[PDB]
Image (cartoon, rainbow over all chains, first blue to last red; front, side, top):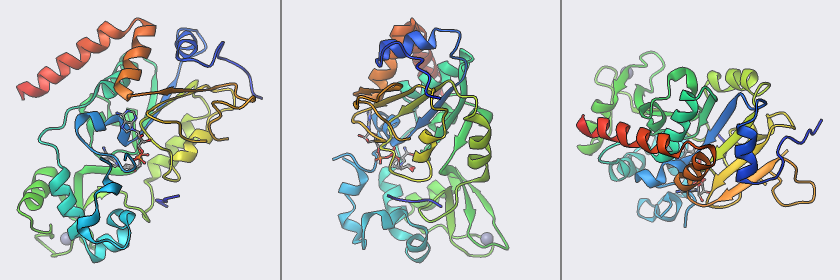
Amino acid sequence: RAAXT
Amino acid sequence: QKERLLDELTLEGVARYMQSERCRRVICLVGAGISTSAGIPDFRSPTGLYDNLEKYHLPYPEAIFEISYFKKHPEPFFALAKELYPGQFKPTICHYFMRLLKDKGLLLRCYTQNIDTLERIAGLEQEDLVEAHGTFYTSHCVSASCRHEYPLSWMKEKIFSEVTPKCEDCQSLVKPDIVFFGESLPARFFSCMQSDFLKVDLLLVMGTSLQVQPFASLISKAPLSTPRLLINKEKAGQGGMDFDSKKAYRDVAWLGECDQGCLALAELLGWKKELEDLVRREHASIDAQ
Ligand SMILES: NC(=O)c1ccc[n+]([C@@H]2C[C@H](COP(=O)(O)OP(=O)(O)OC[C@H]3O[C@@H](n4cnc5c(N)ncnc54)[C@H](O)[C@@H]3O)[C@@H](O)[C@H]2O)c1
Ligand SMILES: [Zn+2]
């Protein structure tokens, strides 16, 4: 699950 | 509660709902899948970027789009940018379907994960858009004290000359205004999310695998009675999407090409001619330069 905070 | 607004969980049902007085505000969530037919590859497709990054010898694929690695080693990203940059940006039938939604007064907002600016080019205004992951259109020096802006032409000249873009003033790395993995989404994303979804009557999700967060979780932000239509080559988002369980009541999956899905939906609404005219006219205008 890739994440751009 | 979970009111049932669709008569049947089909594209036809969705069209019938859209034709009803209840459907006033549509929110589109779109990803790389709506631009692949324009010539821009996605991440996951078996053609996808993640299947062709071997030559860059990354510790892992996603690293090429991670901010730390980019700041340490920007070269792979810009090489990939040199290879992937289309000869021309033309919006797809899908983009213009969203434009048509705007012209019909149905479009509340388009939330996009894409950075190709094709939504703007298709004629969606800045007010109509939430560019959740930024854009390639403008660029900025990474120095906090300088933050010099650079236009797309400057960046393209740098990229095609195979020179790593450096600020002509403070000499810092120049980065496209893309939200890299590990970076924060713009404030507009969250504010618009806080305002729009309490009044959305229909969620149209197109060309995304719904893997990247927090964008994907947007689907859970809609009211429980709000119908959600996925137009995508495969099922995604499974408050997540529920297409096939016995408890399915509002989610519809139309599997195929985004352009074809938008054509079918437009046809069901009696908009096909309008859509085709819009696409041809706008394409002609673009070609005329
Ligand atoms: N055009 C762009 O700006 C671009 C290009 C490449 C990657 N990205 C990033 C990839 C990232 C994740 O978004 P996401 O959309 O989930 O990429 P993704 O690769 O994770 O998923 C794309 C989804 O769309 C589907 N798809 C691809 N082509 C079509 C088509 N013609 N018709 C229907 N479905 C199709 C595909 O099966 C997949 O499920 C975003 O943050 C983007 O910024 C953007
Ligand atoms: Zn600078």
